Amino acid sequence: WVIPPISCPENEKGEFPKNLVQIKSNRDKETKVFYSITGQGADKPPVGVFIIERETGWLKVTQPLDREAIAKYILYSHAVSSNGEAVEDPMEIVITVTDQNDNRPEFTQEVFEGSVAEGAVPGTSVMKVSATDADDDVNTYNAAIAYTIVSQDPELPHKNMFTVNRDTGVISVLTSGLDRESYPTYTLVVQAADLQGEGLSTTAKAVITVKD
Amino acid sequence: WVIPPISCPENEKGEFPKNLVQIKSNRDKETKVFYSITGQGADKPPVGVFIIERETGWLKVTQPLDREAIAKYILYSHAVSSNGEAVEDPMEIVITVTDQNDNRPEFTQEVFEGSVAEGAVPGTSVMKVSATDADDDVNTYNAAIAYTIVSQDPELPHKNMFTVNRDTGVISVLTSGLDRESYPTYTLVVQAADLQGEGLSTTAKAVITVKD
Ligand SMILES: [Ca+2]
Ligand SMILES: [Ca+2]
Ligand SMILES: [Ca+2]
Ligand SMILES: [Ca+2]
Ligand SMILES: [Ca+2]
Ligand SMILES: [Ca+2]
């Protein structure tokens, strides 16, 4: 009647409800026992995410879960005999929702603005782009972002004028050739990709003005 | 002394080892107990994926797991007094590895080949591409594949000569205008992505020959 922590992944597909664990009281030998659960996700909102079979004691989940909505449920199980007397003290059940990589990284803006002096030596820091990821950055790689440049417009004097640091999102002058007179602004297409650059991804824009 | 099933996600990061569950014998009261585990993942290959502190009974996992290598471990715990008599019947512990989308889909071939009659009416089935995904297709969407066409070469008489059913991978003639004399073959770059098209992806080629 001890109960260990319980885990469920989010976004489970398939037939519902699904078994989590069978609750049991020792007093089952001396009398007939009925089981119940209380708390948010049980008898309070969100009602009915978790249910328990009153006779067998099977705790179940009734629907897919979403770790970015609710990462943890605290429930309580109850054990009542047919005479109407509690035969256990209500027992705490902790349900942890585990993560799936179901969120694309997301830039903090959709157009970032920076500027750079045409005279800047190659390897001069220009500006910083940034993305966030709603997935579990503490236990997984589902939120580990890597920045990349996708395209540059215009592609002149050539098409690698700038570079981005994949960890920090800092954009730097890659090569010399910046000519305000001949092209006054560059528009980069930047990409954030999770799983260390290898996962889901999104894009945004960075607009670079060449100063005097 | 009964152990509910245990879950652990694959590819966990952070410090190791990590607590799973505290095992304990009741006779803990009468005498001092030492705790042990056996099985594949404990004392047999893979040795040491799971360990247990012998006095506290804390069962731990020592490294990241990989569902696609081993999805399920069966271990036994043991409880021996300091007098050297077993104080519990060995307990089966089932550890379930839950999946992460950490496998790109994989085309069954690098280059698929097909043919079509230039007279073929738009909507004519041509050929089929196929891919598999090593992730968990029973419980998750991490292996749910959608097929798209990425590019066509040549892009003549225009670029959407064909189309692909996103569920079946059946490529079909989309428009009229096939002309063997001018454009004898098409090279299609096809893509398979999981999370129903929204996820990890790979590409392969489909070369279509235009027949009389
Ligand atoms: Ca979610
Ligand atoms: Ca998630
Ligand atoms: Ca993510
Ligand atoms: Ca794996
Ligand atoms: Ca996997
Ligand atoms: Ca996959």
Image: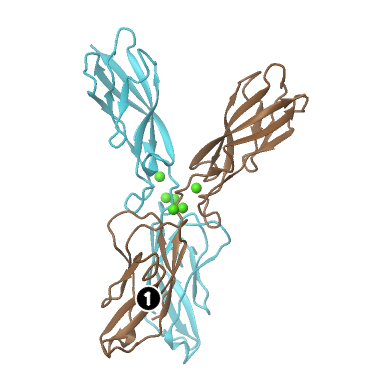
Chain colours: A cyan, B brown
Against A201, residue B14 (above or below) is below
**Percent position of residue A210, x then y:** 28, 15
**Callout 1: SS:** strand
**Percent position of residue A76, x then y:** 40, 72
Looking at this rendering, what residue extends furthest in the top direction?
Answer: A181
Against B104, residue B137 (above or below) is below
- Name the residue located 29 percent from the left edge and 13 percent from the top edge: A177
Front position in the image: A140 or B131: B131
**Percent position of residue A185, x then y:** 33, 15
- Name the residue located 30 percent from the left edge and 17 percent from the top edge: A209
Residues packed near mark 1 inside 10 Å, few (<14), some (14 to 19) or many (20 plus): some
Circle 1 residue: A91
Residue A45 visible within the image: no
Chain designation of label 1: A
Query: Which quadrant holds residue A115?
Result: top left
Residue B121 visible within the image: yes
